[PDB]
Image (cartoon, rainbow, N blue to C red):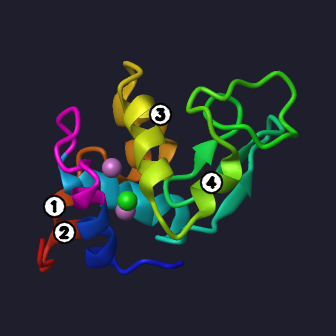
Amino acid sequence: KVFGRCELAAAMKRHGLDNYRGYSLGNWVCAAKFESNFNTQATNRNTDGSTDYGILQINSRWWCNDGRTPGSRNLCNIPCSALLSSDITASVNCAKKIVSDGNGMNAWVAWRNRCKGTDVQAWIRGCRL
Ligand SMILES: [Cl-]
Ligand SMILES: [Pt+2]
Ligand SMILES: [Pt+2]
């Protein structure tokens, strides 16, 4: 499922990401834009042999079990396949443990390089929330 900008914002807001640990909704949407281009089915192989999964490109080295990442953790206690659902509940729930880790949204390189310090609330601009 490829979300719409304001569709995704609404869904994330409905799941409690707006201002979660201080990160306004715009950050979470901008993160999704530059991670998966809003596509729940996005997958991408990392250099280390891990894979990034879903709307926020959650990664198999620490966060989920994909059955093929040697010496990884499943800190969110889910199959990585669960992050490719058209229902974003597990992507959001796992992002909430990721973002609490102490690194914040810096865990996402896309957010750090493309969203951090930008007018991120442009990404929610015009949406009925
Ligand atoms: Cl839900
Ligand atoms: Pt929820
Ligand atoms: Pt939902």
Is residue 14 one of those drawn in magenta? yes
Dot 2 alpha-carbon crowd within 10 angstroms: few under 14, some 14 to 19, many 20 or more: many
In the picture, the disc for residue 124 is 2
Residue placed at 41% from the left, 21% from the top?
Answer: 101
Give the spatial CA distance, label 4 vs label 2: 26 Å
Dot 3 alpha-carbon crowd within 10 angstroms: few under 14, some 14 to 19, many 20 or more: some
Res. 116 image quadrant? top left
- Residue under circle 1? 121
- Residue under circle 3? 107
Give the spatial CA distance, label 2 vs label 1: 5 Å
Where residue 80 appears, as percent x and y from the top left, is 68, 47
Label 4 with label 2: CB-CB less than 8 Å? no
Where residue 107 appears, as percent x and y from the top left, is 47, 33
The prevailing secondary structure element of the residues shown in magenta is: loop
Q: Is mark 3 within 8 Å of ligand 2?
A: no
- Residue under circle 4? 82
The mark that comes first in sequence, 4 or 3, is: 4
Residue placed at 22% from the left, 39% from the top?
Answer: 20
In this rendering, does residue 119 appear at all?
A: no
Give the spatial CA distance, label 4 vs label 3: 20 Å
Q: Is residue 66 above or below residue 76?
A: below
Is residue 59 left or right of 68 when viewed as pictured?
Answer: left
What is the magenta range? 12-23
Give the spatial CA distance, label 3 vs label 1: 20 Å
State the residue in front, 118 or 129.
Answer: 129
